[PDB]
Each structure stands twice: as C-alpha cells, then as structure tokens.
Image (cartoon, rainbow over all chains, first blue to last red):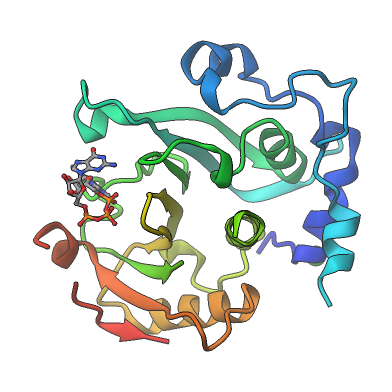
Length: 58
Length: 175
Ligand SMILES: C[n+]1cn([C@@H]2O[C@H](COP(=O)(O)OP(=O)(O)OP(=O)(O)OC[C@H]3O[C@@H](n4cnc5c(=O)[nH]c(N)nc54)[C@H](O)[C@@H]3O)[C@@H](O)[C@H]2O)c2nc(N)[nH]c(=O)c21
Ligand SMILES: [Cl-]
C-alpha cells in the first residue's frame, strides 16, 4: 500500500509545488469562482502552515 | 515532478446552491489530483468549509465515483455520520481528507469518499463506504476515524445505510 501518516502529509505541504495553482485553475475560474482563494501567489500570508499545524497537535 | 504519488486518484466536488437545477445538476466537478503536493495546491486555493455558502457541500471521492446514492459504488453502501467553531470544523474536515488520501484505512477498497454538509442549524461530516452489510470493514473504518480525528466521547459516530436515508434516521452501527 502507498500510504502516508499525517506527519508526512503535513510536511510536504511546505513544498513549492503545494502552493502553485492547480492545473485546472482556468476552468475552475470559469465554473466555480465563488470558492477560489489566494489568487496572488506573491502573497503567502494566508497559506496553510503545515509545520505549525503539526506542532499544534500534542 | 518529484511529487509524492497517492495510491488513488481523488476528485473534489462542489454542490452549489441553485434551486433552478435538480440536486444532481448542482454537483460541480472542480478537479482531480493524485499526488500529495497537488492536494495541497488545491487546498491552498479553495475556501475552507467555514467560508462557503449555506446549503453547499464539499465532497472528495475516488475517481469515477460520484457523491450520490445513484452511483453503483454507493447503491449498497452507507456513511459514518459525525454530528457537529470555524477553526474546529475546518481542521476536522482536513483531518478526514488526510485520512483518505493517506490511505489510513486497511479496508481501502471499501472507501468511496467523504462529504461535509454546511447548513444553518448544524454541519455534518460523513465518510461514505461501499458495502453497508460489510460490518467488518465498516467498523474498522469507524475505529480509524475515531482514533485519527481524536473524537472525544462527547460527539457521536453512527453508521447509516443510504437506503434508509433516502426513505427518511436508522443507525445500524455506533462507535
Ligand atoms: C446525498 N443526497 C442528497 N440529495 C437530495 O438533497 C436533499 C438534502 O440532502 P442532505 O444530504 O443535505 O441532507 P440533510 O440536510 O442532512 O437532511 P435531509 O433530511 O436529507 O434534508 C431534507 C431537507 O432538505 C431540503 N432539500 C431538498 N432538496 C435540496 C437540495 O437540493 N439542496 C439542499 N441544500 N436542501 C435540499 C428539503 O426541502 C428538506 O427541507 C435530500 O433530501 C435529497 O432530496 C440527493 N438526491 C439524490 N438524487 N442523490 C443523493 O445522493 C442525494
Ligand atoms: Cl509515511
């Protein structure tokens, strides 16, 4: 089985590829604009912090 | 490249609130992904459950399985229902998502997807499984959730058949 525990999944969240836009971003803008967020990649103020999320659990 | 592959392909569905359409027509297929990084890419650029309109749903299901009773993968199936703070809800939803894509369940084939209902009164988070009469699989999945989500004895965890749901609730398993 190809599996991952929460620790590793959270760790990979801080990869650059975890912040770049989805492949279908254009079609997502055309079909469901109301649910989209963080459209400016330059601004990572509201980016998910996996290291903190992991640390918050104890 | 160099992304970490997932065991399965997952599809995020968004149930829009549009009474000009039937319930099935409201189901909007957003996109699919099959690596961990692509999941976070999607997650970082869609609103959490606590920020989207009332009467809408987020559903993550395996590729080629629609989040509905009519799908052949759900016909004989059921769901573990978790009855329900903005932060608490978002994190609980995320933890369920990470259980799914991380393949935390031993009976992986029995996993179909997860649905979060956002309603005014309360908010439901449900995990759908393929065979409701497969008690072994259903219970194993149930235990993994309670353990993973760290659900206290405060909240309940009840399994409901889709057939009993559509007839309007009977819970056949409780944990
Ligand atoms: C999963 N599912 C739902 N529907 C449809 O969505 C309604 C609410 O579901 P729901 O999942 O939101 O249930 P609850 O709010 O917990 O309570 P619950 O007791 O189930 O809700 C009943 C209340 O919901 C209202 N309602 C009816 N249609 C809709 C709808 O399209 N969207 C929403 N948000 N509410 C609806 C209805 O007037 C009543 O007040 C169901 O009643 C089905 O019609 C499905 N239809 C098909 N064909 N296939 C499906 O797999 C399916
Ligand atoms: Cl791992």
